[PDB]
Image (cartoon, rainbow, N blue to C red; front, side, top):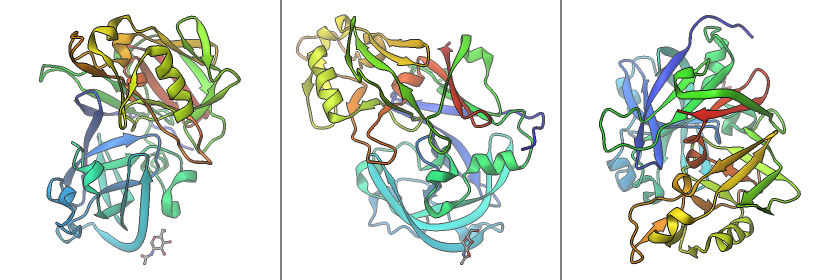
Length: 340
Ligand SMILES: *[C@@H]1O[C@H](CO)[C@@H](O)[C@H](O)[C@H]1NC(C)=O
């Protein structure tokens, strides 16, 4: 390891409280992309100029064109990246990547196959995996390990702030700090849990309360802390018992409640380290209306994550909006503080 004096921040955009992304530059001169920063994956990719326009997703996103980069280095190795909600495929390339102030030589996927569902619903183009090299497809070095290698970051950590959405332009959608936290977006103290293992941003969860009754994950279970997931997710069995306690109808791939019922829905707590992490109804309901004649989506959905990672709860954007999150690679722990 080597610690310098820099921290660097990335400004994020917030789309409808479901997508949080910022800007990176790839190549010389820079080609800019909107990318999700995702603690649940370890690869960088962006759509490629070599993606058939019969993939409608490649008609609607920014495409990396290697033929316009004087700093491109060929590799060409095929890879497939499986995400919870979809899959992309392409080949490895190397170029210079601009993220915050920071310039790093990085191996990434040029995606040539990008399915309409879900990528036509993406405001972002690509992904910067903030996971460990142990999960990296093609054993490629993740961008954060390559940034640590430079020895410029004050600390071997990064931090996520996800804001509530705005009707304003002037709202900061979110912020990643590389090498630190920003005390301007949290208050009180960080409270830390140690990872199960190095190699996955996953921690032990001791319980899940729905009011006063600890009626879920009663023994113990796993929480993946997933900056790239929109929702809080548990296992189909876990959720159908959560969603019974709340009084919510199962639809295709979300649960709903009558909009008028939304505000009187109970608190949901998550026991992590020595602290209860409590979300109000306002925190997990898309309160779009108060009518008995409309339906309102919950920001807790059902996801069966396959082994070895799973089966596990995932704490995504619904949870990070309330709790500023620090990802400590030096001490293999996660710190939560109350976001402001
Ligand atoms: C692709 O990259 C890896 C990573 O270092 C390297 O070991 C491999 O031989 C490369 N292949 C080509 C054809 O450039």
